[PDB]
Image (cartoon, coloured by chain):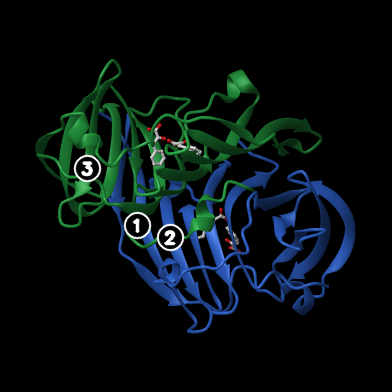
Chain colours: A blue, B green
């Protein structure tokens, strides 16, 4: 069971299997620096009920596993009738952060098994299935050559699951300012 | 007289429409602009995009070099597929695309060269902002809202909001140096 790359950043595409009528397809960008033990994710939050809250949330989250504190910048997009979107930002938020969203050693700590191989985003990929504890199964697809992440499946794709795709992973230097 | 845009700026963006019509999408992504390099990068689900006419929803990363007059697009198609499970999304990378690129999506001097007037101040994204209104000759009006203290972009309005406009918001603009690799134009 392999590690993830020491640092990576990618656009991401986030969706569901199956796609139910109120499921959203979204995008953003994310950064994971495992040396600093820190990540950042910018995008429209998925899932988020506009039905129950009255709005769609855009979020930028900086999760610092070294200090155990996350920081969130938030904007709300509400629907009004005059039919328009009403932008309002919410308070910044902090709270506990036990580990990164994908810990570098996740496949070793949760005892992943190799389920086989799948073409994902036009690349050949290793499927690594592992059980989140008291939460359910997950599959992480790693590029079967470079070892960088292609797709993150949270749940069982055969019944119900979140999917996050990473189409342009860069393993390059991340400037300090990104995690300011 | 209107200001120049910041020499370099990058931000998450949220992209939408006024008014929101049935097929209109709210999307998000990230964008980088370097005016000394005469280059820009935008990553996101393309908005607007006709899934009805094409068969899919497009995610794209585009690098547009106004200096070399060339663009590079990385493309991934998300298609709907009927399945035993109801239906599911199928990702399909398309070929990378290259081609001509005339000018940056938001040129630094755009307010100056297109003769923008100061129409007032407004709070945009919780910040006091200056509104600059101008005409894109042969196309329609625009308003660009700039942070009134820092001069950075906050909201780009393409069209007239009270009838039909696209809105792009920039909630976390950074004036930090942009590493060269961001504009590498390889997946
Ligand atoms: O799974 C997703 O698509 C998300 O919503 C992740 C996320 C986390 C923090 C800020 C924005 C998006
Ligand atoms: O574990 C989560 O809750 C996540 O949001 C994971 C994730 C990772 C990368 C981009 C978006 C979401
Ligand atoms: O206005 C938008 O929301 C866009 O779609 C801009 C864009 C340009 C190039 C790649 C991705 C998104
Ligand atoms: O004018 C356009 O066509 C654009 O795409 C402008 C833009 C600027 C910043 C982020 C996304 C799109």
Indicate the secondary structure of the residue bearing disc 1. loop
Label 2 resides on the chain identified as A
Q: Height in image: B182 above or below B58?
A: below
B128 relative position to B73: left or right: left
Would the CB of label 3 be found within 8 Å of ligand 4? Answer: no
Label 3 resides on the chain identified as B
Q: Could you say where residue B148 lies in the image, as x and y percent from the top left?
A: 15, 52
- Ligand 4 shows up in the quarter that is top left
Inter-mark Cα distance, 1 to 3: 14 Å
In-front residue for pair B139/A162:
B139
B14 relative position to A99: left or right: left
In the picture, which quadrant includes the N terminus of chain B?
A: top left
In-front residue for pair A35/A164:
A35
Q: Could you say where residue B34 lies in the image, as x and y percent from the top left?
A: 38, 50
Q: Could you say where residue B33 lies in the image, as x and y percent from the top left?
A: 39, 48
A163 relative position to B144: left or right: right
Residue A124 at least partly seen: yes
Circles 1 and 3, Cβ within 8 Å, touching? The answer is no
- Name the residue that disc number 1 marks: B172
Mark number for residue B145?
A: 3
Q: Could you say where residue B127 lies in the image, as x and y percent from the top left?
A: 20, 54
Circles 1 and 2, Cβ within 8 Å, touching? The answer is yes
- Name the residue that disc number 2 marks: A60
Circles 2 and 3, Cβ within 8 Å, touching? The answer is no
């Amino acid at each position: 069971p392999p590690l993830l790359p020491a640092r990576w950043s990618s656009a991401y595409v986030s969706y569901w299997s199956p796609m139910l009528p109120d499921d959203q397809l979204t995008s953003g960008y994310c950064w994971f620096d495992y040396e600093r033990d820190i990540c950042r994710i910018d995008g429209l939050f998925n899932p988020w009920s506009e039905r129950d809250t009255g709005y769609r949330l855009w979020m930028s989250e900086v999760g610092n596993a070294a200090s155990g504190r996350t920081w969130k910048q938030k904007v709300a997009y509400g629907r009004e009738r005059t039919e328009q979107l009403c932008e309002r930002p919410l308070d910044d938020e902090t709270g506990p952060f036990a580990e990164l969203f994908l810990p570098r050693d996740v496949l070793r700590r949760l005892g992943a098994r190799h389920i086989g191989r799948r073409v994902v985003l036009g690349r050949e990929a290793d499927g690594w299935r592992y059980q989140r504890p008291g939460k359910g199964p997950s599959t992480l697809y790693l590029d079967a050559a470079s070892g960088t992440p292609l797709r993150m499946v949270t749940g069982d794709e055969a019944s119900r699951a979140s999917l996050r795709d990473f189409p342009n992973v860069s393993e390059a230097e991340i400037p300090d300012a990104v995690f300011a």
